[PDB]
Length: 446
Image (cartoon, rainbow, N blue to C red; front, side, top):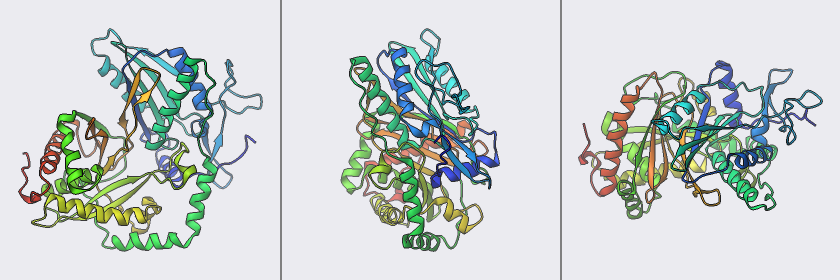
């Protein structure tokens, strides 16, 4: 039973291949956190974590290679409650579960100290053969404020699964504090999700998608950076984060209402317009993440199935910002209709450095996490490695946003990211304030 060999998802397989190239690197360490506005009980939250992890297969997994050098996933339950043992009676390693408690209340700069701690953690390798590929810390910041850090290996947890985890952790915590029965985990099955992907690869639809993507990028446009460079390996990013209050972000909501487009499309159009104005390029490429989750089971299965696809956009002279939004939606229609095809498979068939642009990741709405009084607001710490730039947004136009520019350190210094980020957010807001305006005429800061 413990010897059941689980197949990897497409996303996991690609992470595994990439990791092999730099076996002891930490470039696939990613993370997020919850900013929590009220006091929590660490002992109870620690028990909540043990229960949560036990019910989350991906967080109890390790990865090994079979006799032919092919990877597989192995499920390793945590130790029994109260046990100090680290391997089971048959020698199977137990998934460890540790919630660190780091009291920074009283330090000169609790928030800055927490960030430094999280950066140090993210730079720490997590060997794939050791089960429980995550790292958890509860910070006490003072004023009753906390920060819950979830660090993971990319291979076990994607953006969608971070939200799944936080909601489950809080649900268990509330139950324990209340003396209620812990609601049963409602997570789906990874094996079924993988079987779904295999079913896809076996269907005629696979070929239709292959033809669609390859045809769209025959000319094999060279990936370009905002900097002029110059791309190489995907590396852990330098992250610069900017908070924008509702007074600054509401305008995105108004532009969405006016154009009839979801606000994420407005952001994507904004990035396209910004690239156009920066480089003069008529033909711009941005890359867009999709969840890779198809069907009810997939939607509730913590894991790594995320996909990344190239969005090719023509920005023509005289076009209004509203018009660019329309171009984005037309391009997205095609992308979504062929979303099952792996971005990695497309690059592989095109050769070279593949096709890509800045990753534009507008995270889906997540309800504030309720710990039974205290509330947790999620923010990204690092979304993953990049050959160039990831642009990550969390929040909504109404509630305010966090904008993270995550740059490959061989391409950007932190100060470069700060400068580019500021110019972008101001330009985006200028565009959003009047979508009828001509893109080529909109004010762009030096």
